[PDB]
Length: 330
Image 1: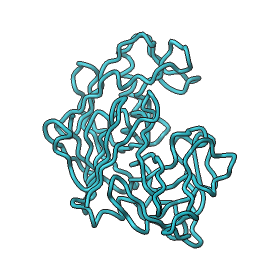
Image 2: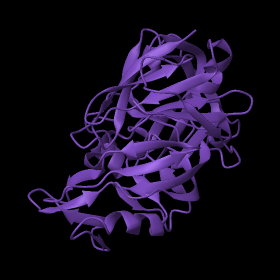
Image 3: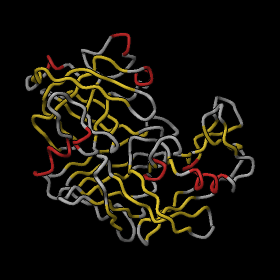
């Protein structure tokens, strides 16, 4: 089997991407944030605290003939931006882009933190990291990809995120029309439950490439590119007026700037992030100070190849017995 679904930016900055997911019988379609950095599929629901729902589409398990309470199971998760959610668990039929999993754990939110409430366009998350990170207790549950894997034509999914435009998540096949040149594959460590890999270095603009190992995670659920302070300083030093602002919470730059590109290494291959992808616009409405898309990972504890990096590439998440990651230009 295979699946293919379009993923759409939630706003003009590509702050996140949503992908329609069919849950239950008859189908209830919710727009979920596919997140290769976590492993829980959770949704706004009929059980969510009413004051914490503001415009989201909810899953109502009582209206699904295939929903079953997973007795005794609870979940609770916290994300890297400080947001969180928790609740109980159903199993139900879940389909993405024509690919169907029966008995998928659908984690129903009883509580969500303020930033989720405020994100009216995100109806939940669909985790695509390794199932060892799934938070369901006392019986850990498998991700959608883990459940679908055996049935897929090939045990892979791909992320093809658009810049200020829709893109595609495919399951079970590699669309050889969706990228240019060849796919370069690179080793993955699953020791921390992430799609963790090591970039071979970087360049700023038209500058020379610096060969240096940068361990980090391919994370579709994180907006920006978070890299070591040395790398980030070298980038922003090429933008007149750019500075790190403690009050804003990262590097800002004059909105009048033309940003240089940023290149990262994948083995001997190179992915180029155009400067425009690094612009996240005014820090507040009407400001001439703009927020940067490359930020320091210092104090996160891990480097994160988020959407800013991933949207510059066609990315293969290869879930073979020994997982790997592939990157191609597009």
